[PDB]
Length: 585
Ligand SMILES: Cc1cc2c(cc1C)N(C[C@H](O)[C@H](O)[C@H](O)COP(=O)(O)OP(=O)(O)OC[C@H]1O[C@@H](n3cnc4c(N)ncnc43)[C@H](O)[C@@H]1O)c1[nH]c(=O)[nH]c(=O)c1N2
Ligand SMILES: *[C@@H]1O[C@H](CO)[C@@H](O[C@@H]2O[C@H](CO)[C@@H](O)[C@H](O)[C@H]2NC(C)=O)[C@H](O)[C@H]1NC(C)=O
Ligand SMILES: *[C@@H]1O[C@H](CO)[C@@H](O)[C@H](O)[C@H]1NC(C)=O
Ligand SMILES: *[C@@H]1O[C@H](CO)[C@@H](O)[C@H](O)[C@H]1NC(C)=O
Ligand SMILES: *[C@@H]1O[C@H](CO)[C@@H](O)[C@H](O)[C@H]1NC(C)=O
Ligand SMILES: *[C@@H]1O[C@H](CO)[C@@H](O)[C@H](O)[C@H]1NC(C)=O
Ligand SMILES: [Mg+2]
Image (cartoon, rainbow, N blue to C red; front, top):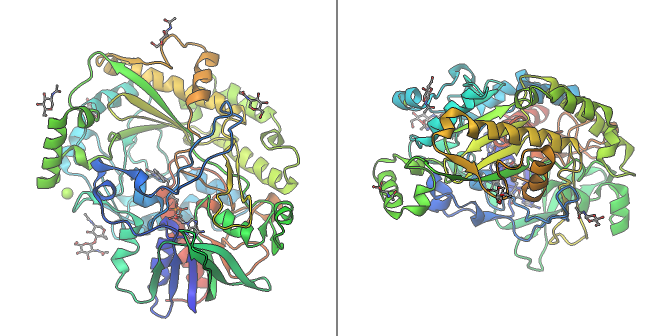
């Protein structure tokens, strides 16, 4: 037997396995669906970014009722290190009120102040060079960035010149410099912290910082290329798991843990393990003939992501070099790759297609003249209208609680609802951080090789379109500001300056929005059981003993920011919770 078995070797699972195996008396088995990465350039080198190397195959959404019934390919990692292995390395904490709100939903021990020690413990920040900090407007507060923890993060050591135009344009339209976006607020523009190891200017993914770093430990066991297919019980006690080869060989193996089973299989994986195991909504489990171990209607409910919109541009006077120089100028690309190979300088330190700066804004910063109209519309509408009729009443109660918390965030000048980015080339990105829409992820069969049904339900809550239209208009203001006008941008079809009304703009958005930036969360939510929760404040699955959820399935709702930094810090926190319960060193 092992002390602990962890299902999924992504950010959360490897962070937890690392910390638990600090005690040589504790043995851990991590079972991971994907393989070990091969250290290929597309993983290690930011400018060679090739995320598609390790996407989970064969996942498609249902037709999206709020997006003209489009079906989309679903993106999530299948690799040791999970999303950290293949993500764009953007390393950002949420805002204070995200964590405070999670506590106020009925979760003792959750707040910004309780998470800050774990953010610090998780990481080592390496400052940029002084010349780059001064030239680039890079600032930080060293008092709230960790100096001793495993996750290395820093910045690229270069910026494209057009990023200066965009910074100044953003400041011209009311997005000022942010001292430190890791300090719990991020209203304006800042350099993107990047999960890069500055010694080699390579990706610091969880495979490296929470497995390779400690891989001499005989008590830290990994089994790549295998799927956890079921949790095994003795009564209501979780005692082990069944696993199969990911590749579909007709073989099943049982393995047992003396203390606990931890699920770390991600927003789209954890609810499937639970449902196949009889932990889930009795209606679904009964329809598939699965015996009910714990009747939890929240499992696979409450799916959230952070939608994205790519706006195309043409320019009369764009500045050289820019990110698109790497794809259209073989001489520039070769010279930048030679520069990286020699002295680790230049464009290849930036994740391909990204720039170095970004902006985040509250609803009142996006829409100073109309945010109170959006809040009124959202306040007037019953929470229940965002969910199908016959949604479990407990799940509706938890959604109403989340919705009330998010409407307080809409009123708050210090909480973000949207992100704007320009990579310096032919497109800008606008991200909707705080959707009120909620989706589902449900098994369709008892076959553990069958994809679940994934329905994002993007844009089903009509408030989302009002927020997202306001974010689009703020992006347009940046591109129309003096410092950007000198590059001669214009929106290209299917957008364009000739789309002036909300109706005109949103009809194109409805056709172009991507439901997902692979930020899937919240499908095994940490809320009281009577609010449709799946886990307690200690991340224990209701109705069973010895079973926790570590991956971002547990989150109640999306952050003002992208998930990775909090995925690491939440696993650091949970490792201490588990150590305390079991008296571990
Ligand atoms: C392409 C892309 C790009 C981005 C991002 C993701 C992706 C895929 N994200 C999101 C972020 O990386 C993601 O939210 C976290 O990795 C989630 O961490 P978890 O531990 O919850 O799951 P994670 O996805 O890391 O790990 C879950 C693991 O479980 C495994 N698994 C699933 N089912 C299993 C089963 N039954 N048995 C065994 N193993 C199983 C999977 O193979 C996977 O490795 C991101 N975030 C951010 O902050 N910055 C960014 O730049 C980006 N960009
Ligand atoms: C990545 O973070 C680790 C952890 O802080 C850094 O590791 C330190 O490395 C130095 C010199 O390499 C050693 O003297 C220390 O013993 C290490 N500390 C720990 C806590 O392991 C590493 O330096 C970081 N990378 C960069 C670029 O700073
Ligand atoms: C989407 O499909 C449903 C039927 O599945 C239909 O009622 C609806 O009109 C369609 N929506 C659009 C935008 O075409
Ligand atoms: C940095 O900010 C100053 C204004 O304080 C501005 O003049 C300059 O262009 C900015 N540079 C970049 C690279 O953002
Ligand atoms: C291509 O890049 C090279 C190397 O930096 C530069 O000298 C040249 O002017 C570029 N050509 C064009 C057409 O941009
Ligand atoms: C509106 O602008 C777009 C983008 O340039 C273009 O596709 C379209 O033809 C324009 N409409 C008219 C009527 O000119
Ligand atoms: Mg230095």
